[PDB]
Image (tube, rainbow over all chains, first blue to last red):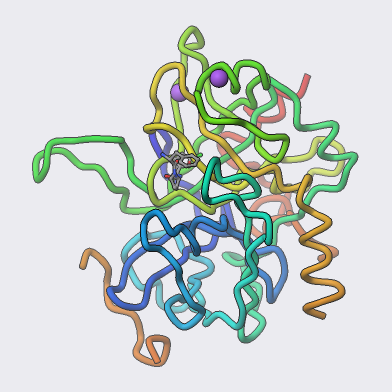
Length: 259
Length: 12
Length: 28
Ligand SMILES: N[C@H](Cc1ccccc1)C(=O)N1CCC[C@H]1C(=O)NCc1ccc(Cl)o1
Ligand code: NA
Ligand code: NA
């Protein structure tokens, strides 16, 4: 996360870290949507251009975390993956269209002050809230900047980072890039004229873009961190998987096939 | 290697 | 889940985090 701040304890209790067993490393963010289901970006698991094609046993999910590198004894819960489900029309060839994946946990995770699921949006909540200018919140452990001077500056955070960002008008998203944008994406970030900055960055992939509904005061995951060109570049925006647009696939995966 | 080691039961 | 999106350390005890007001204020 670029130009964010340290999260408060328990601020994002659905935040999930995707962790490579060997070598032990952060792969991506993710989010908890029930006691057995974790949502992330397809490209966190499958990206042939980078020879990336992870199997269940390659990965753990760590839930309830705050510190990036510490093992948070008595707080985090580390879970093994039962199954990975990638959207069958995930377009890794061109533009990361439908950048979404589910992970089933081998065992349900116990909820706590630090571990709690986020809601997924229904049509009405998405229609009300996914409006240009409305702000959501992005969280992750990814890099603090696109570039820095090695062993002199600092590019990675000690703990979970948070930034609030406004949804951007679709023509502005489209005019910011040569990549083909789809209805399964929205973009977010401040314009150069606006005062403020902020973006996701490498390692934030797959984590949640959330909004707090003013109707029922619940947090809804509207987006998944998907792609950008650079991080926090002027005139560029971060692009997010439109969770509601893919919810019928989510429901199918959970309701008919996985339950 | 920035990462504090995980309990062994998880890496199995 | 019935209690989705309600954080134990915030909504469940009617405490706000330090920047959620920024989100509310944008929903005009
Ligand atoms: N630079 C290409 C741009 C691209 C976009 C679509 C199709 C191919 C390439 C990119 O973004 N990616 C490459 C694969 C993973 C993804 C990534 O790095 N996502 C992280 C990120 C930063 C900000 C937010 Cl939002 O997500
Ligand atoms: Na364009
Ligand atoms: Na930008």
